[PDB]
């Protein structure tokens, strides 16, 4: 069966402590529609109860210790999470955990540290003389004590921070100490993009490297995870990420599929990341997200023949995770660049019914977003579910592409004799509707095919040579399959 990932959260999920129970209750539904793996949000204790998990305080607290004024995380308790994972696994759905290793947030106390300021546009350049600051770097875990790990964090485990508690000023501070320097290799944007936010972990420090590998193995084992989503990969030493993934795989004996978030609209830089990590993990296809967004926002003027230009999926199809939108590109968020609603079903047909890429469905697109703008994403599950059914049951076999018009483009799948009645013909258009003659395979000659989306009511008959004349409405999608 075709694999399909689902990101199971949106930025504005409520702080009601019931998210793990929601997931548990949705397991049957997710398996029924064709989801084969779920990416869950960071499940460890953040600097406050309402943190989404990207300001992680204690990686060993999965919602069971009294820290930061709460036992549960935003999403629920550890036992609730283990019950959700149990329900998914009983329905043959895998679970990938989000891993936030670039920084730590919410230190228990400050420490005195010697530091220099650096140029925000070129972090290799020092711009001040050294001086003393008070940085938030002492992590003691008073609610956990030494349960699971007795490692405590201090300033010397970090490379820098962006807040001095003594003068109350925000600058990028690089710490002074033995062999201190920004890590390499990382993105060369801003000269060196190791520093992002909070207290930056030093992956040159051998105890830190060793402890982080130990945590990785503990986390995969405690929750029985099947893979990972690596946060902020452009900001973490590439050879460390390569080796950390290898160490967890070696210790568990599992495949541990891994996808890294390397946020850059440039395939060449993404290819460098793949090379530097020995092709041992996939990346999200950022360039394809931006091509889909561009097509959705040009009112029909985009040249649809160019949708695959510059994308990771056109060059490295087995190492790409394709997506339409996520918790950062949704309205009001940090990487806001939402695919407009009218085009969203066409974008989902493009990533779910083509042979290359491992597609991701976004929670926010299925169930709607609950942010406070006048442009939230509406719930589109009724439009996406028929496309997921097309992937689950019909998108198999040889593919033929028809990117030969500036508005109307399409592709077909001949089907596979081992999946009964498989085969499909998809057409999308960013402009007026029309038709296209496409080949679906002589083995499907004389069959009656119909649009599974319900957008067109007229069925199409495949001629004796394996060709059909397919139609599509304006600004729409049609996916024809065996009636
Ligand atoms: C989002 C994306 O970002 C990056 O992408 C960039 C990209 O790489 C770049 O290229 C560019 O992109 C271009 C593109 O290339 C172009 O082509 C295209 O066209 O345009 C784009 C541009 O749009 O730009 C991109 C954007 O910059 C990155 O590459 C991606 O990977 C990334 N995506 C992923 C990564 C993420 C990060 O993990 C996710 O980000 C999300 O979450 C972030 C974290 O929440 C969020 O960050 C923002 O918000 C943060 C809050 C902020 N932190 C600062 C704030 C601080 C304090 O608030 C500060 O904290 C320090 O100081 C505190 C003291 O004030 C101290 O706390 C102590 O005191 C307090 C009081 C104590 N708490 C007490 C209170 C209580 C509560 O009642 C009690 O509970 C408690 O008991 C009590 O004690 C505490 O205990 C004390 O410790 C702290 O300790 C101290 O650390 C901090 O240091 C500050 O940094 C961030 O800076 C801000 O950025 C992001 O916005 C979210 O998006 C993302 O989701 C991932 O997918
Ligand atoms: Ca370093
Ligand atoms: Ca870093
Ligand atoms: Ca067009
Ligand atoms: Ca057939
Ligand atoms: Na670092």
Image (cartoon, grey):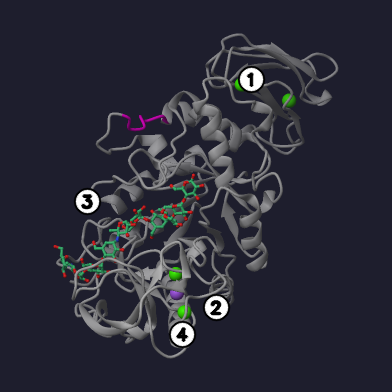
Asked if the residues shown at circle 3 and circle 4 are in contact, with their CB atoms under 8 angstroms apart, the answer is no
Segment tinted magenta in the rendering: 375-380
Which corner quadrant holds the N terminus? top right
349 or 464, which lies in front?
Answer: 349
Q: Is residue 106 left or right of residue 149?
A: left
Residue 398: % across, % down? 77, 36
Residue 60 in view of the camera: yes
Residue 183: % across, % down? 50, 75
* Residue that badge 1 annotates: 407
Residue 205's mark? Answer: 4
* Residue that badge 3 annotates: 15
Residue 226 in view of the camera: no
Q: Secondary structure at mark 2?
A: helix
Q: Secondary structure at mark 1?
A: loop
Ligand 6 shows up in which quadrant of the image? bottom left
Q: Earlier in the sequence, mark 4 or mark 1?
A: 4
Where is 197 relative to 403, above or below? below
Verify whether residue 377 appears in magenta.
yes
Q: What separation in Å lies between label 2 and label 3 (alpha carbons)?
A: 35 Å
Residue displayed at 35% across by 44% down: 333
Which corner quadrant holds the C terminus? top right
Q: Is residue 268 left or right of residue 464?
A: left
- Nearer to us of marks 2 and 4 is 4
184 or 374, which lies in front?
Answer: 184
Q: Secondary structure at mark 4?
A: loop
Is the residue at mark 4 in contact range of ligand 2, meaning its CB lies under 8 Å from it?
Answer: yes
- Nearer to us of marks 2 and 3 is 3
Classify 10 Å Cα crowding around label 4: few (below 14), some (14-19), many (20 and above): some
Residue 251's mark? Answer: 2
Residue at the extreme top = 458
């Amino acid at each position: 069966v075709n694999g399909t990932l689902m990101q199971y959260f949106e930025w504005y999920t409520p702080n009601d402590g019931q998210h793990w129970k929601r997931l548990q209750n949705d397991a049957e539904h997710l398996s029924d529609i064709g989801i084969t793996a779920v990416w869950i949000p960071p499940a460890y204790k953040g600097l406050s109860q309402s943190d989404n998990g990207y300001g992680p305080y204690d990686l060993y607290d999965l919602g069971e210790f009294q820290q930061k004024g709460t036992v549960r995380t935003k999403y629920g308790t550890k036992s609730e999470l283990q019950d959700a994972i149990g329900s998914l696994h009983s329905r043959n759905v895998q679970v990938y955990g989000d891993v936030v290793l670039n920084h730590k947030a919410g230190a228990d106390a400050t420490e005195d540290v010697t530091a220099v300021e650096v140029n925000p546009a070129n972090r290799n350049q020092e711009t001040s003389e050294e001086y003393q600051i008070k940085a938030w770097t002492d992590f003691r875990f008073p609610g956990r004590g030494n349960t699971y790990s007795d490692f405590k964090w201090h300033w010397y485990h970090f490379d820098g921070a962006d807040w001095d508690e003594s003068r109350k000023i925000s600058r990028i501070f690089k710490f002074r100490g033995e062999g201190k320097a920004w890590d390499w290799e990382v993105s060369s944007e801003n000269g060196n993009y190791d520093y992002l936010m909070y207290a930056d972990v030093d992956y040159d420090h051998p105890d830190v490297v060793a402890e982080t590998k130990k945590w990785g193995i503990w986390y995969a084992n405690e929750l029985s995870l099947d893979g990972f989503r690596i946060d902020a990969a452009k900001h973490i030493k590439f050879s460390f990420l390569r080796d950390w993934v290898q160490a967890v795989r070696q210790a568990t004996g599992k495949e541990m599929f891994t996808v890294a978030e390397y946020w850059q609209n440039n395939a060449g830089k993404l290819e460098n990341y793949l090379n530097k990590t020995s092709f041992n993990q996939s990346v999200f296809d950022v360039p394809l997200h931006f091509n889909l967004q561009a097509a959705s926002s040009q009112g029909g003027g985009y040249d649809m023949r160019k949708l695959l230009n510059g994308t990771v999926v056109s060059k490295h199809p087995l190492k790409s995770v394709t997506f339409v939108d996520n918790h950062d590109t949704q309205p009001g968020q940090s990487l806001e660049s939402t695919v407009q609603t009218w085009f969203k079903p066409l974008a989902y047909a493009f990533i779910l019914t083509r042979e290359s890429g491992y597609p991701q469905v976004f929670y926010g697109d299925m169930y709607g977003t609950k942010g406070d703008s006048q442009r939230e994403i509406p719930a589109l599950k009724h439009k996406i579910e028929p496309i997921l059914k097309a992937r689950k049951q019909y998108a198999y076999g040889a593919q033929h592409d028809y990117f030969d018009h500036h508005d109307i483009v399409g592709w077909t799948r001949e089907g596979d004799s081992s999946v009964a009645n498989s085969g499909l013909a998809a057409l999308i258009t960013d402009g007026p509707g029309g038709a296209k003659r496409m080949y679906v395979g002589r083995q499907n000659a004389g069959e009656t095919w119909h649009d599974i989306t319900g957008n067109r009511s007229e069925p199409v008959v495949i001629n004796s040579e394996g060709w059909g004349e397919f139609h599509v409405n304006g600004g729409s999608v049609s996916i024809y399959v065996q009636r």
